[PDB]
Amino acid sequence: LVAAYPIVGVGMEKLIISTNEHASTDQGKTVSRATVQDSNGESWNTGLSINKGESAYINANVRYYNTGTAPMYKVTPTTNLVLDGDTLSTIKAQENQIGNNLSPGDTYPKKGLSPLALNTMDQFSSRLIPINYDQLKKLDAGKQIKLETTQVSGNFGTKNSSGQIVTEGNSWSDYISQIDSISASIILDTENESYERRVTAKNLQDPEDKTPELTIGEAIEKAFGATKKDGLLYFNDIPIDESCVELIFDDNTANKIKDSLKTLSDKKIYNVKLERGMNILIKTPTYFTNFDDYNNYPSTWSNVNTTNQDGLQGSANKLNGETKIKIPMSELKPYKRYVFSGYSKDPLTSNSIIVKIKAKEEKTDYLVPEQGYTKFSYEFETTEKDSSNIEITLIGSGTTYLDNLSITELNSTPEI
Amino acid sequence: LVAAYPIVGVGMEKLIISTNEHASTDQGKTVSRATVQDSNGESWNTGLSINKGESAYINANVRYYNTGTAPMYKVTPTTNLVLDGDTLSTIKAQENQIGNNLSPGDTYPKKGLSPLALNTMDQFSSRLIPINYDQLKKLDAGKQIKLETTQVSGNFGTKNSSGQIVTEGNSWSDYISQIDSISASIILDTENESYERRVTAKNLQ
Image (cartoon, rainbow over all chains, first blue to last red):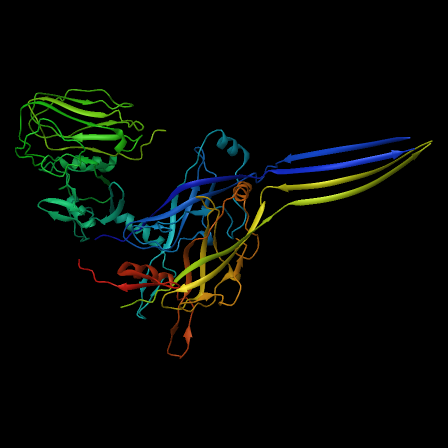
């Protein structure tokens, strides 16, 4: 029920420009004699010119990488060069920039090597790619470009009766669209890697089809090789729960799950029936706070108490006091919108000091709804390499701990 | 339990550069007479120029060599020219630089010969490979380049019922990745030689 569907992305490393300028230097010596009179002269001729029409050549440094569950033989992408809300050229790479092999979970070329270069737009490798003069002025005035993937073309492998395989005329292109008509797209993002899978779905409109269906918790169990450990789900001894990760929905999927939850009797987003067209992100968190064990924390909290520190639904202490952790910015990445999220309890008042500079130094009271558990989450911006700490502090009157709290990445967020 | 898997590497021997410079020399003689007065002049015109956009052509000296347990018919590598933490061009060699045969434990060309040359980037052998001016200044300021292998493409051999073999459409490329999914890579290095083998393994999962 998982379909082999290899994803390709193109990554930018460096950009080199080059100017088509034209220089010259001439020296002349003249002498004349006439009958008495004479003359002698020394002439210099410096010359510099540039003629528009192919006025600036360029070259780019790229590297291919795979993600998914297939190889991809003879991969060939296409790139679309933007400069400033616009386009400049569109290149399908020639024979010299073909990507030969690509194992799943890998890059091309191999890791201990240098990147790939591309410079021409013709079908045979001639005629270096030009940039006209106004784009050159926009470039030197301070504006920079990026890269963009649009499609790839590659071939799979299949063995005949003869005992070998053949890779010719077997395009992966005409197996793209069919899969994206039937499947749901689930992506995972951990701290170093990312994985994109398509899992098959079940249409409820027409009754003739018989496709076996499941739920999103079982879907993440089946797509990734996930081990059910004691009710939790674990992926390479990394916990993935309905509570220990951060889920991201787009608006149509969010609305479908949200209005489908009300007829359901359980308030879990792991037991919802899977639908046809979805995009579900699951991001792992950076720093976890299970007070029992597995707490990747540099310093340890204050006024803690171990009575059923199981995480959610059993955090079992209601007293007064203070918790505080100071952390410098040196360990974490700068200039990234970090998101801090945890859960609730039954106190009456609690307040949260998040004193991080260049960011939300607003501190608010808790506004606890009831003894039942609800999440809470705030956003902030990371500064640049300061031992001046971010210091989380929670003062409470009616609780000392609730055993779920974390901070996580929320990437694709730089500042300058 | 040992899989035939020939390794190819590219070795650098020498690098030649060449400048696209443009020289000229002119001589003129003038004489004039008018009614009494006269004049006579001798003019020289030295000229030297260079225009960027294909300002420095180059050529490289390479030689192929095998290591492993297979031949490799019609070998064709790709090279990736770095200069200083960067890249300058990427060439899959044309028809004139194909490597024809390669026995295991051998080099191409044979040992009592001179190396191979390559100079062009086009698909048909034209348009010598250019280097722009800043790289030329980095070169003459004292920085040197190297070579790099990324992939090769070659063909194996198989005999049919007809009693001969055929080498066409039988790529070694689509037998690369499968072997590197199942095998362990063991290499030996002695004082003159080196040997790279892949031996098949057993999954315990």
